[PDB]
Amino acid sequence: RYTKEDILKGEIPEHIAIIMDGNGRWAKKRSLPRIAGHHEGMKVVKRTTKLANELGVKVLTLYAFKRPKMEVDFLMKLPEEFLNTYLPELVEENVQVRIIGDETALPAHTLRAIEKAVQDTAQNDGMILNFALNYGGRTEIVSAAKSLAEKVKEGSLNIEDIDESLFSTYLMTESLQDPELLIRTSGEIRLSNFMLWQVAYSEFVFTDVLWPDFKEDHFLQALGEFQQRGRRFGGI
Amino acid sequence: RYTKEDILKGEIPEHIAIIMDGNGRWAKKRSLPRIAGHHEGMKVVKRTTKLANELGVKVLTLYAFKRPKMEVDFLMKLPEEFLNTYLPELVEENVQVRIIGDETALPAHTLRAIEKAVQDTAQNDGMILNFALNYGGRTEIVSAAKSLAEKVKEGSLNIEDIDESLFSTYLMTESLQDPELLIRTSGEIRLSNFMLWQVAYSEFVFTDVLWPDFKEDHFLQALGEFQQRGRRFGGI
Ligand SMILES: CCN(CC)CCOc1ccc(/C(=C(/Cl)c2ccccc2)c2ccccc2)cc1
Ligand SMILES: CCN(CC)CCOc1ccc(/C(=C(/Cl)c2ccccc2)c2ccccc2)cc1
Image 1 (cartoon, helix red, strand yellow):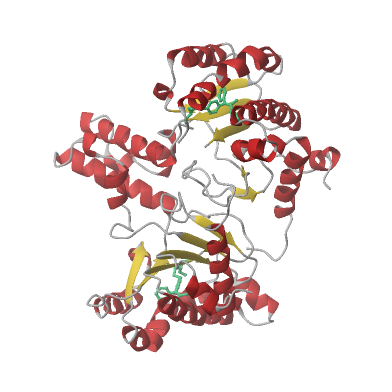
Image 2: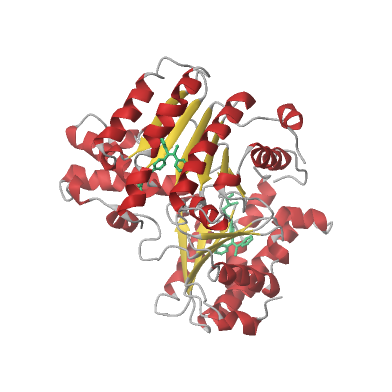
């Protein structure tokens, strides 16, 4: 219903966090192998990234969350295929690439590619493409707690100086703003341990559309849902 | 659609956390004053509490979240009216009453009534009636962080002993289990800073029904939604 020219008339969130899910369900739905669904999801990452760069979005976060060895090794090579394919098309769009999570659970060849893509994009000031690999909201909160405790132990930080502001700075999204919008696909209505502190005041849009089928139109429909939320009477 | 005898056939969550919202919208909808809507919400708390005690629920958490002086003072006296009216009917049902949040933002007369109701219900082992007054998820997380930092400063706790388990114990819901189900009313699809750590793996049910209109039937329908979620193929 909502077209591109209707969404550009409306407010564009500055930070959108999408939960990409349903790659496997989409492979079964199409009688394809699972790794094919993960490949298609990798391509949807790019379509969405370009669309969000067009719309004025400033930060865009992506998260994708047992599996046999083959599928795990295929997944841990998708970042390299994604960067060896679309990194020139992203530096051309002034997009900064960053990664949040535990990088130590990636193999070296993948981390080198990731780090190179980050460093070739640090001098940019356009949209931010934020990837969550091996990311746990609870483990982020506990690690911020533990670093704060380290600083208290050394004596460089007094316990009465800790507040919501200082605590946000110790999260993996420190130089970032909280997501104005959260999107979740595959039909699940949960958070599944993603950015718990950050989605406190975030509008949640849920949708049964699987992540490979989430192209330009469904993203626009999600933005129309958001914008209509913004323009609801009755008060609060 | 789902009757009581259909819901009792299915799985009953052990911990349900409801976000009571829309008391004001319900007062306007019925041309009543706002304080009347808060009174009706107070009565719905009891209907729901009895229904959940019937269904086998073990813990039931309730949260209700600027206003003119009159409405604030009326609200801070609703706990006493609620306890002076329904506390015998709750001790008769073996319900334990507890309160989480900042109690120091209540006046003394209210805190004395609350504390008395807690102490007259400590010797019970039935359902738990958990009230969130002046409760902030972010402030709960930061306070747990700060107590942990205090224990590290004194030397009674080493920083390598802190984990998701130990961190849960420092939240206001320490002796409690995470909510299997979260319900939110008034049509809003957000969390609004409620139990961020706890709803990590919690099924969220949203409903436009205002909290005064949330009687027995809508609670059953929410439980049917949950139970149908539990019995969905396609996998994960
Ligand atoms: C098997 C290892 N898992 C943990 C189980 C963690 C590592 O898996 C992942 C590997 C790649 C990605 C990923 C993309 Cl672009 C992807 C997006 C949508 C659907 C599927 C893959 C990516 C590529 C480059 C940078 C950042 C992200 C996400 C998780
Ligand atoms: C004005 C003060 N606010 C903060 C703005 C905090 C204090 O307000 C509140 C006062 C009472 C309650 C409340 C009940 Cl039962 C209630 C439930 C549903 C709808 C309206 C009221 C209650 C009674 C006894 C024990 C526990 C809860 C909740 C918040």
